[PDB]
Amino acid sequence: EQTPLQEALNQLMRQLQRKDPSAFFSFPVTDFIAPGYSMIIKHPMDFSTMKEKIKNNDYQSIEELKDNFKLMCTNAMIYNKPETIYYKAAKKLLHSGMKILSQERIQSLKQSIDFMAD
Ligand SMILES: CC(=O)c1cc(-c2cc(C(=O)NC3CC3)ccc2C)c2ncccn12
Image (cartoon, rainbow, N blue to C red; front, top):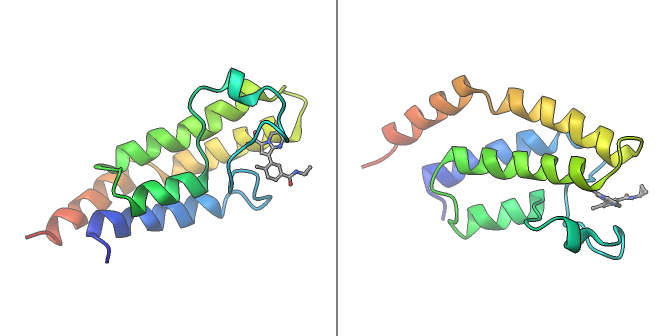
């Protein structure tokens, strides 16, 4: 039902989402709640979309998930003005998420994935 890589990606997801208690990054931003979003942000990302990419096996590496997570936070800091709650929340989430997605945890998880293979 899940490969070791999928299991590892799903666990990181849960860890990252716990750093978004406001649930602002849980779901895709739409043009209705953020006017002109689709004209400014060319590659949207959110936790629910990351969740489908894992289930659909779109990720070949943990680094890909980390890139998507950074994209999530980068999009929010580009679209939202610094005085907004969403900008501040993106900065807090980026800092907390990058500690979760440290080189040491990523390398540790990659070692485990290889040990569970073949
Ligand atoms: C990531 C980001 O840029 C973003 C996220 C949201 C958003 C807000 C709420 C919410 O609860 N809003 C009420 C507190 C006022 C719920 C879910 C989402 C996806 C948002 N809304 C407008 C502009 C930007 N954003």
